[PDB]
Amino acid sequence: TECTIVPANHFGPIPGVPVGTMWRFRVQVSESGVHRPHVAGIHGRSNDGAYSLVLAGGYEDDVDNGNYFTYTGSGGQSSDQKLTNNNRALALNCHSPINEKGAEAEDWRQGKPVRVVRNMKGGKHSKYAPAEGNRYDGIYKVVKYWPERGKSGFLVWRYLLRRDDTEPEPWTREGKDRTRQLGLTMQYPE
Image (cartoon, rainbow, N blue to C red; front, top):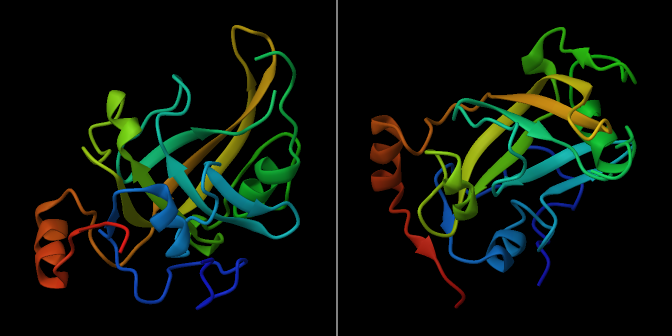
């Protein structure tokens, strides 16, 4: 059943789903409303913004630093990516006018929020990935985005996101203490 407590185009935290929430399977992640697409790694609308993303490995030039991370858009390498569809959505989140050249946020915190989920498949490059399942790590914002052409010569769209959430990161001592207070357990299908 699709999440109905908030609309599909809801920006920001999902009511009742705290930072640190864990689900074994993507279908539960979707049903919770935190990341609606079952398979795709980003949810957005090209004229509104990006609502959520799942970090599951992605590309080799991406680096996960926990409180911040870099990220690569979709499409294309055999052809150029374009600042359309979800690449555009994510760029629109940045506190800056949309720019085919890339842009940096004026005040990054005034950007539209992005719900970030880390999935265990990211553990092959990131020490922040959960060992199992999927974990909601809170709200991040787009600090900047830019195009680049790597070894294939084709263009990819790149993003830097930084955490802006009042609850601590689940991997920290403070996060672990919140997980305890909230009684968070790996969630399974009922």
